[PDB]
Structures are given as C-alpha cells and as structure tokens.
Image (cartoon, coloured by chain):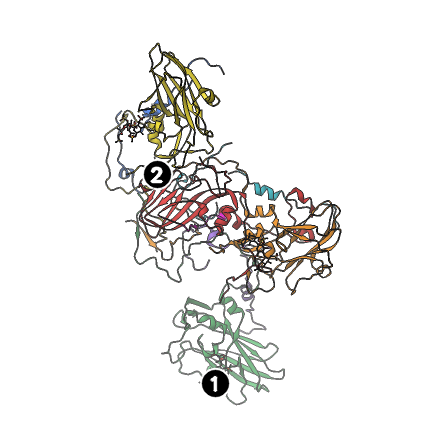
Chain colours: A red, B cyan, C blue, D purple, E yellow, F orange, G green
Amino acid sequence: TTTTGESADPVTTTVENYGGDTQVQRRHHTDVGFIMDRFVKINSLSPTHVIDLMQTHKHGIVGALLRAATYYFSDLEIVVRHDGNLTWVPNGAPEAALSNTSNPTAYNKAPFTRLALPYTAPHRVLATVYDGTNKYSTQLPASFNYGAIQAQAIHELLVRMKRAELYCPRPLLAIKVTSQDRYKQKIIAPA
Amino acid sequence: SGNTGSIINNYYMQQYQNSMSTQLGTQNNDWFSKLASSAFTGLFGALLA
Amino acid sequence: SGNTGSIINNYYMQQYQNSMSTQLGTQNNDWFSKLASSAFTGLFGALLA
Amino acid sequence: SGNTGSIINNYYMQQYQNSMSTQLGTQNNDWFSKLASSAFTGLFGALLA
Amino acid sequence: GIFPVACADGYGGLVTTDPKTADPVYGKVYNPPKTNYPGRFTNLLDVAEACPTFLRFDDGKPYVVTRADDTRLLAKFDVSLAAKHMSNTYLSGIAQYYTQYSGTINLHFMFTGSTDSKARYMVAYIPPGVETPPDTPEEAAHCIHAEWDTGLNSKFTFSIPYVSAADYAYTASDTAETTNVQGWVCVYQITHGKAENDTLLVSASAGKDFELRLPIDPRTQ
Amino acid sequence: GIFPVACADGYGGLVTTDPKTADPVYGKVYNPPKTNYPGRFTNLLDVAEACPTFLRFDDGKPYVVTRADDTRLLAKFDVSLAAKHMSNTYLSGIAQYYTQYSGTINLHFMFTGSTDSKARYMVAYIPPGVETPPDTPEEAAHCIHAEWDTGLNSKFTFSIPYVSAADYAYTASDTAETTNVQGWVCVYQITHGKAENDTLLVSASAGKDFELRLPIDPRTQ
Amino acid sequence: GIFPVACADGYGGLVTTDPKTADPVYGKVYNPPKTNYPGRFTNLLDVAEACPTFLRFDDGKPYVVTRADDTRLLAKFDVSLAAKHMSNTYLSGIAQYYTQYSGTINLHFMFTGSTDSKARYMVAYIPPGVETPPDTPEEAAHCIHAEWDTGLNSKFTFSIPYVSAADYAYTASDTAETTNVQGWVCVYQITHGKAENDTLLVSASAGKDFELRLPIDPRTQ
Ligand SMILES: O=C(O)[C@@H]1O[C@@H](O[C@H]2[C@H](O)[C@@H](NS(=O)(=O)O)[C@@H](O)O[C@@H]2COS(=O)(=O)O)[C@H](OS(=O)(=O)O)[C@@H](O)[C@@H]1O[C@H]1O[C@H](COS(=O)(=O)O)[C@@H](O)[C@H](O)[C@H]1NS(=O)(=O)O
Ligand SMILES: O=C(O)[C@@H]1O[C@@H](O[C@H]2[C@H](O)[C@@H](NS(=O)(=O)O)[C@@H](O)O[C@@H]2COS(=O)(=O)O)[C@H](OS(=O)(=O)O)[C@@H](O)[C@@H]1O[C@H]1O[C@H](COS(=O)(=O)O)[C@@H](O)[C@H](O)[C@H]1NS(=O)(=O)O
Ligand SMILES: O=C(O)[C@@H]1O[C@@H](O[C@H]2[C@H](O)[C@@H](NS(=O)(=O)O)[C@@H](O)O[C@@H]2COS(=O)(=O)O)[C@H](OS(=O)(=O)O)[C@@H](O)[C@@H]1O[C@H]1O[C@H](COS(=O)(=O)O)[C@@H](O)[C@H](O)[C@H]1NS(=O)(=O)O
C-alpha cells in the first residue's frame, strides 16, 4: 500500500496483500495493568524513606515502562524488611510525624511487612517528567510521592503498582547494539 | 483487573483495599486503542490479481 | 461503624464483642449537625446583580 | 484429572493455575485406545465344541 | 484429612490503624442508659461550621483597631491553616491532624463601636502570583473583594474561595516556602467617622464545602 | 472445639509476581477526579501499531541513500528484534521485556526526494536456509517481494511475514547463532532518475497479529 | 474477633505423591495448539494389548528352533513377569513399576518356515503344585493346553489364565522362592515334516482383563 506519509495517519498493512492469512493474536502480556502489576525493588534506602516511583531503576521492566509514559496513576503495595516497627505517613505530612505511633504503624513480624497503600497525592495524576521553569514558591515537584516510611533500619523495599493507568507514551530503548548485525547474548539452555 | 488470580472475594471492603475514584462529567477514553483501530488497511489504487 | 473494613460477619456474638446499650424513653440526637444545618445562608437586604 | 483428590474448588483461577490450551480445527484422539479395541477376538475357522 | 492452609509471609502483623477487631473475653455487660444525652457531635466539621472562633492580631487581640492615621491596611495574613493569625482558632486545631484540605473558609467581621462611630471596610482575597500583597484598596480592587459599611447589623461574613492548581492543598507549610502558596487576605479601612480606637472582631469558620482528608499525628510527644 | 488446619510446607512465601493482594491499613480515601484525561493507552501493542519509529542505517541515520554507482543493495538486516538496525525502535524497546513473539512486523518506506527525483525500489523477505542474502534483485525475485515506484504518494508499507518452524520465536539472539534464525530483509534500488543523494526513510510498526508473550526483566541493574 | 484455628501436629508435610496442587506465580500463558497430534496413548495397558513384544530364548533369540532329535520340549518358562524369557518384553517393562497384577497374559506363536516345512505344536499351562514341569506332551496333556498345526495362517494365540489362591499375585519374585509361585508354560513339538532349523517366533501381550495395581519405584538409582 502507498499512502501520503506526510499526514502521519496510521497505516497497517497485512500479509493478505501478497496472499497470506493474518492470524489470531492474544495480547494479555502487553496489557498495561497486568505488566505493571509486579514487585520491583528500590535500591537506595535509609531509616527514613520517601516513596517515589522514580527511584525505580531505569532499565528494569517496571521502571523502563513507567518512564515510557508521561503521566500515570496507581495505588500501591510495599514489602519492607526492617528492624523495629514501621510507620507510614501520607503525602503532605511533616517529617516529624514519622515518630508517632498513631500513624499506620506495623509492629515487627518476621520476615518482613507487606502492606496495601492508597494513592495519596493532591494531583489527579502524577508525572515522570515535569517541565517547570522552576516549580517553586531535571527535578520533580516534591508533591509527587506516595508518602513515607520509617523504622530503626530499612534493609529492603519492594514496591508494586496496583490499578495502573498510563498516559502519553515516551521513548523506550533497547540495549545499544555494537555488533555488525544483532545483539547476541547467552540464552538459557540445558546442560 | 491485571495480575490478580484469586477466586475468593476479598475479606476487606473496597473502600479499605483501594483508594476510591471520583468523577466529574472507567470509560472508553482509550486514545491509542482508537488510533490503532483507525489505521488504514486497504490498498490505495487499482488492483490486478 | 468507623474504621472497621472487614466483609465477613464476626465469629463472636455481639453481646461478647461489645457492651450492650440500654434505653429509657442510636437516634438523631446530633445537636451539632442540627446547629450547622440551621446556619443562615441567604443575604440580608435587597440585591442588585 | 490424574492424582489430585481434593474436594474443594481451587482458590486460584485456572488461567493462573495452569497454562491454557488453544485449538485449530481434549477429544478422542486416542490412537492406542482405538488400536486395542480393534483387536480380533474371535476364532478363525469352524468350531467343534 | 483436614483443610490445607498456607500461612503467608508479610501478613499478620499488628498495624495501629488496622480494620479488624480483637477477640472478647468478658461478655454480657449492659450499660447504664445514655438516651438523649445533650451536646453530641459526630463530625468535627459540624462544630467547625457552627462555632466560629477568633483570629489573632497585633499584640494578641481577637480584633483589629481603626487607624487614626492615613494608612488603610488594617491586617494582612496568609491563607494558611498554619498562619500565625489562625493559630488560636478551632479550625486550625482540627486541621493540624490532617494532611490536606480543600474548600471554603469563612471570615466574620463584627463591629464593636458605639452608635455614633461609623466606618466602611473592604476585604480582598489576593491570590498567589504577586510578590507582596497590596497595601492599598485601589490596587486590591482588581481582586475578588467585598466592601461593607457600619449600621444596624454589626456582623459581615465573607467566603475565602479555594482557588488553586491542584485539587487539594497542604494544611502544613514547608520551610522552603517564601511566599504563601495559597495567597493572602487583606482587610482595609476605606474611611471612618469618629471611629478612632473602635474595634472590629474577626473570626473564622468552615464553609459548606470545606474538607479535610488524610489523618496525621504530627505533634512532638 | 475449633476448626483443625494443616499449615502446609512449601507454601506461604512471597513471590514478587504473586496473584494475591496485601491487607489495607488506611481506608476511605477518595481521589481527585481524572475523568477523561487525554492520551491513555492500555496495551503496549496499540501504540506499537499506531506509531512507527525509525530504523538505524549506516552511520546512524533513519534513512538509506540512493546509490550513485552500480551496486543495487541499499540495505540488508536480520529479521530480529535484537538487530542493530532495529535497536532504536519502540518495537524493540518493548520486545526486550518478553521472551517470545509471533506475527507480522510492518516496514514503511517514505521517499524524501524533490519532485524531479524519481526511483523504483524493491523489498524482499529472505527466509532462512541460504548462507548469505542475495545482493541482486534478480536473485531475490524468487522470494516474497514487492516493487514500487515514486510518485504522488510518498510512503509504501510492506508486511514481513512470520514464517518459522515453531509457533513462536525468541526475541533475543543467542551467542552461538551464526546466521539469523528468522532470515533477512533486503531493500534494493532497481533504478533511479536524478535521485542521487536523495533519501528513503524507513520505519517499523507492529502488524495486526504481532504478539509478545512471557514477560522478562533482563537488563543489567 | 477473628476465626480461631487449631494448627494440627502431624499434618502439613510434603509427600511426593500428595493429592494437592502448588500455588501459581506466572499467569495467562496460552500454549501453541496441539490439536489432533498423532500417536497418543492414555493407558499403558492399551499399548501393552495392541503391541506384542518378543520373548527371549536360548542364546538370545526371539524364537525357538524345531528340534532334529527325539526331544519334544521346545521351551519351558516361569509364568512370571520377572522371568528371564520375559525380560525383554514391554509387558515386563511396565510391570516392574507395580507391585501386583491379575488377569490374562497372551502368547503368540508365528511360524517362520518355508512353504514345504510343516509342524504340529502344543502349548500347556502347568499350574503350581508339581515339583518340575513335564518334558512330555503325554504328561502335559492333562493340563489346560492347545495344539495347532502349520498352514495358511502363520500365527496362533493362546491365553495363559490367571489361576491362583489369592486375587492378586506379585509381579516380583522373592529370593526364598524355589519353584515359581504361578507355575509354568511349556511349548512342545508333537512332530514336524522337513522343518529342521525352521523357527517359531513367540511374543506376549496383555489380555482383556490383565491388570496392574500399586505403583512402585524399585530400580537402583
Ligand atoms: O513569645 C511569645 O510569643 C509571647 O507569647 C504569648 O503568651 C502565650 C504564652 O507564651 C503561652 N504559654 S506557653 O508555655 O508558651 O504554652 C500561653 O499562655 O498563651 C499565651 C498567649 O499566646 S498567643 O499565641 O499570642 O495567643 C504572648 O501573649 S500574652 O502573654 O499576652 O498572653 C505574646 O504576646 C508573646 O509574643 C510576643 O513575643 C514574641 C517572641 O518573644 S521575644 O522577641 O523572643 O522576646 C514575638 O515574636 C511576638 O511578636 C510578640 N507578640 S506582639 O504581637 O505583641 O509583638
Ligand atoms: O561506539 C558507537 O557505537 C558510537 O555510538 C553512537 O553514539 C551513541 C552514544 O554512544 C550513546 N551514548 S551512551 O553513553 O553509549 O549511552 C547515545 O548518545 O546515542 C548515540 C547514538 O547511538 S546509535 O545507537 O548509533 O543511534 C554513535 O552515533 S552518534 O554519536 O553520531 O550519535 C555511533 O556512530 C558510534 O558507532 C560507531 O562506532 C562503533 C564502535 O566504535 S569503535 O570502533 O570502537 O571506535 C562502530 O561499531 C559503529 O559501526 C560506528 N557507527 S558507523 O555506522 O558510523 O560506522
Ligand atoms: O552376561 C550375559 O548375560 C550376556 O549378556 C547379553 O548381552 C547383553 C548386554 O550385556 C547388554 N549390555 S549391559 O551393559 O549389560 O546393559 C545389552 O547390550 O544387551 C545384550 C543382550 O542381553 S539379553 O538380555 O540377553 O537380551 C548377551 O547377549 S548378546 O551379547 O548376544 O546381545 C547374552 O548372550 C549373555 O548371556 C550369556 O552369559 C550369561 C552370563 O555370562 S558368564 O557365564 O558369567 O560368562 C549366561 O548366564 C547366559 O546364559 C548367557 N546367554 S546364553 O543363553 O547364550 O547361554
């Protein structure tokens, strides 16, 4: 098929053009809500930690995919391996509140704590990139977070996006290829 | 949903398990699905098969 | 209720789970709700819009 | 099934508990069952009992 | 056999705000009746709407005094539940336990002068976007404002509207904030006739759509 | 008595992709409305179909240049989501997170020359089974191919068919692979008239039956 | 409160043959279709009935040779799935994985001689109770037996009946067993005419009521 390409109108040809038969597709694994729904780890940690999905690694399946969207929304689940008790506080809270027990506080139970937390930002949607001239009264507004946690020590933090919604796609890149033809690597095979 | 495969109904109420969405006016506001389905599939011009 | 979000009915009877209230005569004895709803909202005097 | 003896229905959905089979056309495509049932059982020739 | 069960890791711990209930141990207790006990309240915002409390001005007074000189700005304050002027209100007392708010805040002005004391006032909501609030009624006129005079009715009520970029605003204020994120309210005195040393009491209450969400326990203990 | 239960060994551990949900601790939060927010996408393949991105040729250009000499092969590349030429496409960006694929991949050719520049091209799918791809239109003619010329419509689209032994093919390529398992695509220039230095942009998009299965997290972290 | 539960001692351990299923972790995978794939079998005994395999005689031959001398016993073997003569059959291959059996075992005799070679055979089931099997057709005649001759049809099939004290018999044989618990089968040659060096192939298959129960994993690993 030939078309006026300058218009940018989508064109999808099929093998029928030269005698083939287009087949059946099952696209469950490329479903946004499904694919974002798995735990991902946050590497940097500290006794006091503000939950920010952008601390996710840029090349991990979740972090790559999240960054391939401009705006997003989701609820959250967290797994925290910590010493002592864990206190969570919602978006907008004074850092000092983290010391108070009446905020959701999970008492230590081995081996870690799994929790379901609601979206809690004052915005209708959040962004992975924000073109602010400043945004004050490569930096993101401080209001873009899912609250904060505190314990005597935070050893590990996994985070899971629930009911994820993604808007306005952005570039997603594969590994840079050096070889003359294909990027080759060791694929699993029996001994 | 997406990646939840439990048969049994949840022990906790929905207003606890999740944040509650509000509206001003989940519908078919799927821009990219529309965009993709609108793609031209024919053949511009005359055919000789 | 207030801050209880379990779907499943309680395993223990109510007379064990809580103290039992008695009456002499939970109704609408909400003074402050009445007070607030009675607040004047109009505009005293004539208007020129 | 084969070697599963639980009465209670599974907590997880089938699309999670197992891979899903697809078709192009579990039927009676049991070659060996057919083969065995087709075996000759009579007696070739005349009988004197 | 018996019912198989998977005791799941990461579940079971006590969370101080959990949605479950404990197991009972002492049953069958009937309470003395408290049918129709007076003064009950079920939502903090009902009392916050019905009972306005006072703002704090100058050296610790619930009022503003009419200026004898040619300066017309009587007061200026941050539209913030954490503002110094709101620090003694019931509204700010409740607000400190929540992370976000939205909605209308009402201001009440009650003139206290003698029958022979007269005045004309103006209140304006200065939204964010300007570096400093105007100290002149003429400059503030371009904003949302109301002017009223003295007479038989001693009180005047005005609604500070919620106008912001996000749907919710923080009740607390961050140390990195120079200018108040939600703007200011300026009270002016257009003129007065023999009203020197006469007072204007100002109080605040929650409006019909005022809302507080996300409970928090922030005070030092 | 109470209900007997068997706490089973081998069950209960956290699996990062498990199909369960955590227990809640902070209830009754209502979100700001986001009704009809623009640009939403629910499946990665909808955008992969609607938005073709560019292939990479020679010294890092999204196009191929018409040859002034007597060599007619403009480009040759592996039908592989891991091919150097596909390395900057959105299609390969998504594909790296899946172990297998199947289906149609579409190529788009947009001529960029002036009105007085004309040419005739040919694209062929060389299936596996031959040691090296043909550098001649005459040899490649025996394969599935399409020829088109220049004119009012500047773009031409062709479907690379999925023809393989197994029902699915790997998105990644093993180090032990000499020849590309799925074959090649060869773009030729039959002729041209005053088209020296004129360009042919080439991009790719997912076809109607393109499919990706089996999520994977392979990048070094 | 919550639901009380008694975690029972002695329950919960993994048993390699347990009737439960594991918890899933990777959902929504659809398999390539395998509709109507040929050669399927659902029960080991269907193939054991349909495909007879060969017995092993003398120096490792699937046949018995007609005797040139005046000895008429061609073969004698234990009615045992563990018999040397059955050691290469598919029937014994399956039987080793079960503790008990019951039912009919079928023997097949296929004459291999030239058109001008003729013979008359006899097969007898010698039940247990006698010290050694008879080496004479005359003595074996008193048992359940069948005689057949050579002709247009080259094969003859005979059913070894299950006759025992218990309802089931062991597939394996104990070291303390002198005489075979289930008796013997004796194949005789009544006579022959020019059949010297001509062969009689013998194979076995499961009969209609042959049955194997109680799975076992006995081989050294
Ligand atoms: O230091 C102050 O802020 C002075 O506090 C006010 O008194 C408080 C009192 O401290 C408090 N007791 S507590 O132990 O702190 O809890 C309680 O009794 O309430 C009163 C009233 O406080 S209110 O918030 O103002 O309503 C003084 O008020 S009062 O004593 O008349 O009741 C208040 O006038 C004082 O503030 C002045 O001093 C401030 C700092 O002091 S200093 O410069 O270090 O010496 C100064 O910042 C204020 O501007 C000033 N008030 S002014 O408007 O008159 O200038
Ligand atoms: O070494 C290369 O591959 C050169 O890389 C390309 O530049 C990358 C850049 O490296 C990358 N930054 S990052 O830190 O690596 O992430 C990012 O900025 O993208 C650019 C573009 O990369 S792309 O994948 O080609 O799109 C050079 O492109 S650019 O600088 O003009 O933008 C690319 O031309 C370079 O590749 C050349 O060198 C390769 C190996 O270098 S060497 O032999 O060791 O000296 C060689 O294998 C390539 O063939 C050659 N490209 S050629 O086609 O012009 O010959
Ligand atoms: O020792 C034997 O039993 C001899 O074994 C058979 O060969 C086996 C071979 O050993 C086996 N390899 S494995 O590593 O053991 O797994 C495999 O290749 O199968 C063949 C065939 O075995 S079968 O079970 O007989 O079908 C000889 O057969 S073959 O080599 O011609 O294929 C078999 O003839 C051998 O048995 C003879 O020797 C036995 C003991 O040997 S010795 O006395 O210690 O020297 C003896 O007990 C047997 O009677 C004798 N067979 S006879 O009938 O010809 O006399």
Report the chain holding disc 2.
C
For residue A112, say whether it is visible. yes
Q: Nearer the viewer, residue G157 or E196?
A: E196
* Disc 2: which residue: C4
Horizontal and vertical percent for residue A144? Answer: 44, 40
Residue G136: which numbered mark, if any? Answer: 1
Report the Cα–Cα distance between label 1 and label 2: 92 Å
Cβ of mark 2 under 8 A from ligand 1: no
Q: Secondary structure at mark 1?
A: loop
Magenta highlight range:
A34-46
Residue E107: which numbered mark, if any? Answer: none
- For the image, the number of numbered tags is 2
What amino acid is found at the position of numbered circle 1 in the picture?
Thr
Q: Nearer the viewer, residue A2 or E72?
A: E72
Q: Is residue F114 left or right of residue G60?
A: right
What amino acid is found at the position of numbered circle 2 in the picture?
Thr
- Mark whose residue sits in front, 1 or 2: 2
Report the chain holding disc 1.
G
Q: Is residue F221 left or right of residue F79?
A: left
F97 shown above or below B14: below
Decide whether the magenta segment is chiefly helix, strand or loop. loop
